[PDB]
Length: 248
Length: 246
Ligand SMILES: CCCCCCCCCC(=O)O
Ligand SMILES: CCCCCCCCCC(=O)O
Image (tube, rainbow over all chains, first blue to last red; front, side, top):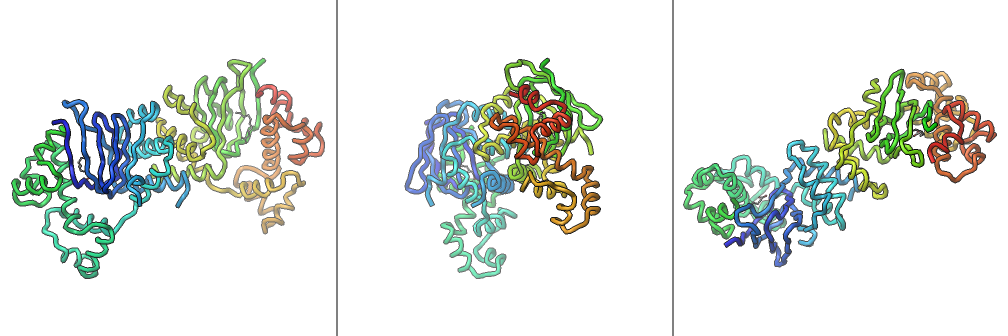
């Protein structure tokens, strides 16, 4: 089957996706968005979504994706609040567009080496999109640091340690209630943050195609490679082997 | 004869010039740059240059020019020093505009200022040896005392200005102001003459004001006197200037 359903995908970096040969339904919050043959998808950081996906060509990769790390996105926010001025709807969180001739050829000669060239390519592209406010919005919203973000970074400093709400609540000078309700006010909780951190790191590493599963288990902090396969399958709704075979 | 010599052109706004159909020799300071057919020219604000320029097709305009006012240049400076972190070769720069970047310049509609700053930033991103430009955009984006003097003069171009009026406006003595302007390699009569003569050139290109109106507007009694001053300064008469650029 050239179709795959992947669950609980949480986007940890602002992501721009280009459906190189796939078609995709994005569910997330009891909603749904379709992304057709040749479109661009701008995914706000922090969303949690599920995906149903159709390959066009079976022998090829599903899509092509660009992810903006924390710095780059801070910069894009600043430059955007200089170029346009300074100032809850899943349709204001995930946006598809029709990639034009000039915007496409621009996407061609994008070499993600000169980071400034990338920020500029991205700004010019943003300038050449209609109804573009809703994208500007999602880039500033997802460009602020939340408390779940402080927790996320403290966990990433050593992904494999055995974390508890007790260690985070010691790190931050407050009690476990403080942390469970601040994280609850962000529509998440700590066991889920840890789970999302390990499962994304595992997916990406599995796509690198140069690590045994047991190593990836160890890298994210999971004893058994078979135990890791169970957790991955339960979370994403596919086994690492099928995920890998669909994405290679 | 479709070649023209224009002297003492003083750039009050960061200028990007595209020799749409002309060839041009630029004399900054005892130095010289030639700009071939289809090139871009980045002119640092505050430079004073002289130009000898030859049209390709005569029934058309010489070039196409973009001038960035203070707001826009401040926004460009800020945005540029977020995205990236005395030499007439760092003040006037010509480059080769590629095919694709040329089409980019085409679909430039200077209405959405955000779209224009974006087009400008993408262009700057697509230039080799472009460091020399970012510097000149920051170099020319700070406020000098000649600038404070310029803004006071521009608030009412037609008054009869002297050093005495400026030295009362700013709390200092005429020596203070002549020497603060001196360390900027200018003087007040030059500042005033350059405002009036630039404003006169631009207005003459607008094709909608009698010469007497332009004279009256810049602060010059006579229209025949203004024509004399213009010819003496620019090296052409307003009529020859207009007929060359229309
Ligand atoms: C779009 C379907 C692919 C599965 C998602 C892989 C990891 C999500 C990316 C991220 O963590 O930033
Ligand atoms: C190279 C073309 C120059 C001819 C006209 C110059 C008048 C503009 C003066 C200015 O921008 O401050």
